[PDB]
Structures are given as structure tokens and as C-alpha cells.
Length: 282
Length: 274
Image: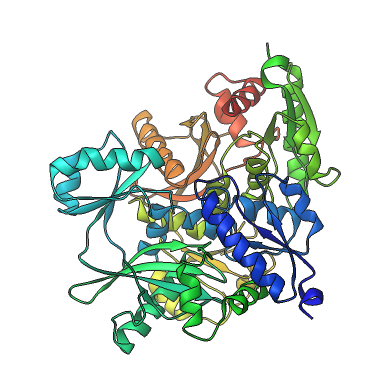
């Protein structure tokens, strides 16, 4: 029985980040699903309950989005307490929360990703323009979809850099590539059917283009050290090339989120998906 | 004052890793220094203590070497307990414990580092030997345990079942220590101040190592090792986010060379936490 198999599970939800509200929604949905499945799940909100009280549990299902939950901190405590848990470890999480460090890992593994430049007051805006070309996208390095602005002149720059400066002291200008954006979800370390972003299955890629994108994303997922489940975002350009965008090591499990979509396209109810995520902890 | 200013401080020492002995040594020295300077420091060894006790301190001086203190685990627990602490945060520490991820990020920031292949059992060497060139230096990714290859691969798998082979290079090994984010005088190794490096080649290496230190997310204090080859080009080797503070340790050398007693070093490191 699932009560035996998993013992006491803590569903880690809410937390201290900007994304707390989304995390409460993921958490509730995951809790209800695990309970329907006969697992002994309990909400654990580390904003209200000391993380030392995790010692009362046999394992953790992490659905804390953003700062605290996705950046290696909560995984740090879980390692320290010797409690197994879902998703990526400390290293991968802390890399995955940083767009530039993720891309350097990707540049460093012979995987395609768009040129970029870190931009911090001191940097010269015409040395950026001449190297990258127009247009570019300005994004906060650490938010791990907020603060983004599209820059198509010298004029567009100064307003975009203060969009991102709210969310981050450190900001990257990345070369714009024209095309369509996709998300590739992961379950038990492997790629699930791709989803075009903006519904989005069918995604608009030939069987061939798709399985090639999934292979590429598998390697991106491994490179950065992600485990279990998560999403890689990618671009296809108007000449057919793929470009890796970013990694997400604790995706949404809200009723509008994309990983449930992709898991359902291959047989998983939402409750089955939740058991399968938790099975990584055995 | 100082008793007032820093409050109750926990010296994180000892622990459960292979480097425990060295940590105990670093820990006893830091505790002694802090206590001489009037700060209310107390030893906190995780082997004898409960995590729930960290909440009794206003700040922590981390001198836990290896697994636990150097890979972000303890940093994670302190972030969540809201305990300010010395040195590098979760990310920098997690990356710094890993020679390849560190070198990857360095490649990616256009900083010099020697070629390498990851090399585990069930891969053929002739791919590696062809690509890097003999001679070559195997080493565990996540920690010495080194050598200079059918048998040397299992000496690494003692420590870590993933190993890296690095293009060996002829030259002089250095280490460049950091305090309050800024680099300190450099030290040759196999004394080592003077290092044997012109004032001008010294500032070049420091400003480079500063960038390598920054690029990896490291903060406050630490060490970057580097090499200079026969033609005078520096190659970065690795980063260390919780260096020794034993009586033979390099960071105390480097800081004495610029006017810090061991005791003023310790206080200066603790000042990162305000």
C-alpha cells in the first residue's frame, strides 16, 4: 500500500518567495492528489514551520517556487537532515536558478544557446549593440517569466533595464532569435511530449523535429545536473535550428501548469503524475 | 564594542566528513582568536549538536571543510533559519565543490583553464589521450586523491565514481586568497612570499583571479589556485570556499603579508556578516 511504501511525506509549499501564492496552489493540488492515492501527505510551509521539523518525515515533495525553493536552499536543508526529496539536488538547483550560469554550463558542453552579455551600469551599451546585434531581450538573471522587455533601438534600452533591475541587481541582454518557443517537460529523468508556448499540443513540429528537440533537451537537462522532473524551454528559429533558453527545476503543479499537460499526453492522470514524481525518492 | 556588535557567534567546526580533523583544527584556532578579540564565540560541532540549536546564535563562522560546509548544505540550513554567516552562499559553494562545473563556468566567462575530459569506467582512453595529450592528471571531481592509466581511475573511485582528466601543463602553481571580496598577495606552492612574480604579473593574476572568483558566485573570503605555463600564461585550476585556518594554512600567510594578525583576519571575516 502507498501509506507503507512512502511513510510520512511532507509537501513543501508556500515559502518566502515572490511566487508564494503560486506555490500554495501547486502544493494544495499535490497534497490532494497524494491523499487520493493513499499516501500520508501533510502540508509543510517553511515560512510558518521551522525547517528543522522536517525530521518528522520520511521524505519530501518540493513545490516551493522561486527564492528558497528552487535555488538549492531547501535542498541544502534536506541533504543536511538526510531526507530524500523530489527533483534536482543543490548544485543543479542553484545553477538552474541562474540563466547566465545555466548557459555557460550549456556553452561549456557544446550545446547551442543564444549569445548574451551581462549588463551592470558600468557596461557600454554600444559595445553590446555591435557584438549581439539588434534586437535583443533584456531579462533578470535570477527570476528563474517576469521583468523581460524586447529592445529594438538604443531608445528601448533604458526603460527595459529598470524593468529587470526591480527583480535583480544583475541583468543579461541576450541576442533575440525569431521563432517559436517550446517547453519540454521531464519525468523520471526523461522527456515528455513537447508543448508550444504563448493550448499547444500538437506543438507544430514534425515527429523528427520533435524527437530531435527532446534529445537535445535531455542533454541540456543532464548537463546542468537536473534530476527527476522539470522543464527545459527552447526556441526554434526560422531556419530550423534549436536554441536552449532556460531550465526549471520546480515547475508549477497548478491547474493551468504545463507539466501536467505533457504528462497527460502520455497516460498520466495528475494523481499518477504525482506518485511518479514522488517515486524518485525511493 | 565587539561582544555587543557581533552577539553570540557559532563557530561551525568538526562535522562528519573526511576533513573533520582539519576542521577541528581550523575551528579551535578561529574560536581562540575570536574569543581573544572579545566576541562571544562558541564551538558548534554538528556531530555533538542538534540543528535546532543554531537558532541560539546571531551569526555563524563557517569553518566546516568538505561535504556539509563547502557544498551549500549548511549554507542552505542557515539561509532558512535566517542566520547570517561567513563566506560563499549556497550557489557558489555548490559549484565550487565541483572542478568541472567550476571550469565550465570559467570557459563560459572567457577565462583561461586547461582542457579536460570527464572520464568514468566504461569509456575508452584513446579518445582522451588523443584529445588532451600525454601526460595527464586524473582527479576526483568533487574533492587530494590525485595521481599522474588503468589503475589510477579506481583511486579516484574511492572518493567519487566520476573522475576528470586534465591536460597537464609545465609551470608554477600559485594560490590567490581573498578577503572582503578583494584579492591578497599571491603565494607560490609545491615559504612562498615573495612568490617570484613581478609586481606587474602579480596584479594581472590577482585581477584575473578576482574575476574567476566573482564569476563562480564566491564571496567574502576563499582561495583560487592557478598555474603559469613556460610562456607566462595563467591557467585557473580550482576555487576553495572554506580554506583552512590551521597554523600552517595559506590564507593566514597571505593576510599577514598585508598587516593582519590571525586575530584581525578572523574578525575581518566575521565582519562580512553585518
